[PDB]
Image (cartoon, rainbow over all chains, first blue to last red; front, side):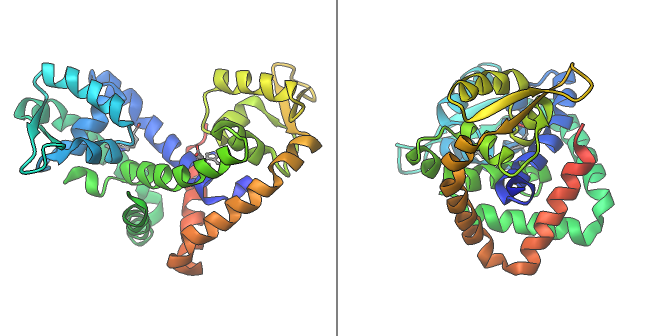
Length: 140
Length: 140
Ligand SMILES: O=C(O)CCCc1c[nH]c2ccccc12
Ligand SMILES: O=C(O)CCCc1c[nH]c2ccccc12
């Protein structure tokens, strides 16, 4: 069976199954899943470009920009001009956004701890290191 | 930075970056990405239920059923009644579908080999084993 060991299919199924478990949580706290991805990606970060935000949130850039339009209207994020290149817009979370997402982030950490507990610390750290190295080799 | 080591974000970014590289290939061979997921998932498989196909292809079940409507019209797949429970429809690839996808599957294997080569055999097998165990623990 081709699909049983094919890496992209394994990554996509593991990602969908683990993420879908947290969806209910995010929505019960009043967040859409994409709002959660944006605010969790910006929490504790210096301002990043729209393109960087689109990559880390695995969301298409036009979709990200419409999302930021409403999140900025609600005071949860802010878009800012870039240092030199003004082809580039930066984005950051505001204090209001951080306060809105902090509890959900603790719940996310607890859920992640549960997902990783059966694997033990060595296998969990190996998995995270491999995924980080793959991202850094394939990001454009 | 919360997002830098958060497992679901790492899985989703690695999955999106690695899969998007093969999209161009699939389309140059005349496949949509979802047609590729269906035919690669059924290749070499006994008939599986629609719900199983939706899970392994990470596609919503109503979307899968519409996709199968057109793929079956093109003779690439076939839906069949289940053994006993006729709440359940099974689906299989046909010979025509297998012949249509076989070359693309070899290209997919080559791309996967390239993705995994820098990690070496031990780290690649550890990654695949961890992902398989996660899927089997979280599938519903
Ligand atoms: O959408 C993509 O580009 C592929 C995502 C990975 C993926 C998930 N399920 C699958 C079944 C067969 C082949 C690939 C997969
Ligand atoms: O869509 C989901 O349910 C989450 C997918 C995983 C994911 C991808 N990018 C992210 C950035 C912040 C938090 C979670 C993520």
